[PDB]
Image (cartoon, rainbow, N blue to C red):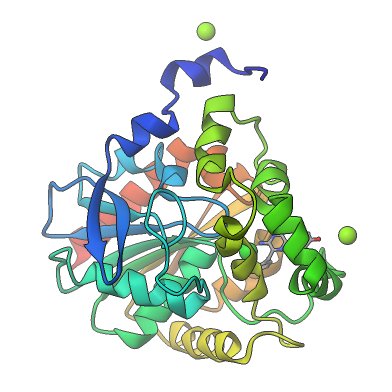
Length: 308
Ligand SMILES: Nc1ncc(-c2ccc(O)cc2)nc1Cc1ccccc1
Ligand SMILES: [Cl-]
Ligand SMILES: [Mg+2]
Ligand SMILES: [Mg+2]
């Protein structure tokens, strides 16, 4: 494979280098792999990836925030180096079951800070809706902010989701690894070095059912027309909560030109007490502007801690 950027290779963190910095813990009938910076545990900043990725997504972002608060970054169940779900189901509520059980083992403070990307933001938002007294602040980006009606730059979203929900979508993902091999690199502006792509491919290198989480995630999409009713209700509930959460400081990181960002920025602006920043990127913006993102998050967390 070609290599691309001598400067990026100089500071690159491979899959094995990242995993060697992680911890593991049994959770319910399985286990979670996670990064835990440990220090400054009076606060906790929990970073949640979404589909196709793992805790590895945050590897160049977290160093900026670790000096200010304990940073904890799980691989969602069935993803990264975590164990598999006991029944092989990977819906939003399955992820939420393992995630919340893991939280109970971490010795968390009363009020937690969440940093969410994409479906990881949905998990944070649903946790917040159900634990409204446990939230210090929320950072979100390229996130599931609301139900999805008509996205101007994705006029075919309903047909594309119908394909993914059909048996053909199963072949695209389980046989051809569509989300890791096609969507992931297409929505990073730079070229990943081979070792970086290998870290994302590793959990899903074999064909078949091991790739189920990457198919189940898009099938959860909260489309008004045809979205899974339980997810649609979850998102409607947490959206209305966020719209009235005047006391809850938020940071929204817009991606320029972005992937979801164009459609969701209006929705993010409907949540009170939001600071707005912008970085270059498509969907997986951590791969294009990790240091700018890390510095913005660090500043935001520092301000939140000063004001309290
Ligand atoms: N994240 C996605 N990226 C790409 C595609 C996709 C699907 C089919 C296709 O032919 C090309 C791309 N789907 C999602 C699913 C999704 C989840 C939540 C919000 C919005 C989208
Ligand atoms: Cl998805
Ligand atoms: Mg040089
Ligand atoms: Mg198309």
